[PDB]
Image (cartoon, rainbow, N blue to C red; front, side, top):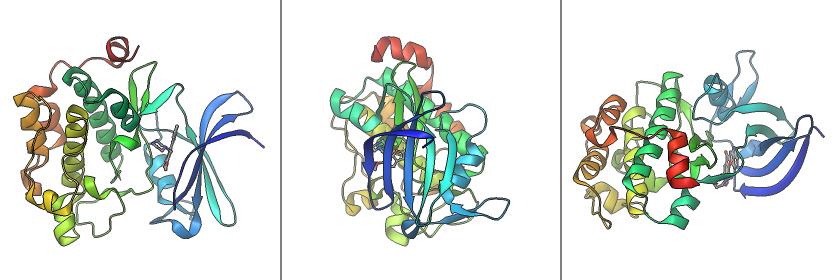
Length: 270
Ligand SMILES: COc1ccc2c(c1CN1CCNCC1)O/C(=C\c1c[nH]c3ccccc13)C2=O
């Protein structure tokens, strides 16, 4: 109809995501089908329409520019919703990027981690909590060296009280969720960011089983600088209140002198 459907990009119990092209102007898009009976949490537009929470969250952040994917349009069907999302081209998610390249140089990890921090800060400033930050949910604009957060289907409105639901990725979930099924938004996000940063500089996640998450002992399987190890272990503090704020992360000595996105593309991507 309005969009030329291309190949399937991924699928799950939630639904299916296709590559697409907007017919009117040949704009690259992603077409995300969301099964109604599998929606974790429902949202509501100001006009009262019940929609998947991802629609609400994306609209709250889909303003101006940021490192968050833009929701271009959305439709409702009898049994599903259809989301039209921005699609960079060429693109590769961070999972495939690390799989092909192995552990990233710290200069490159610094650039990527900084951009993720800026994107997560933007979400929180807009009252949005992603709840599934991980390499698979980060797209790399290979030409511009810019990263973009994707998939808010596990997200929620940001609040200052405790969350008791979680449908994100378990190996990125904090020990307080594993033990008590309870967490606060910001400190749980910082934990996932610690997992992500370890993943970038070591080429794999640090914990596989619940017992390792609860123990919280970080072993580095790759050569990693002392400053980077410190930031990782700080983000992965067992006590949530011991974890750094976003400001403390970006003011950490390891985060100084970040490359610009285009510089990052020139040195590491082209
Ligand atoms: C199971 O696979 C999923 C699940 C959820 C989403 C999704 C995908 C497809 N891949 C899977 C592997 N990692 C990257 C995403 O894509 C999304 C949004 C996208 C927005 N614009 C894009 C452009 C290019 C590819 C993707 C998207 C999602 O929410």
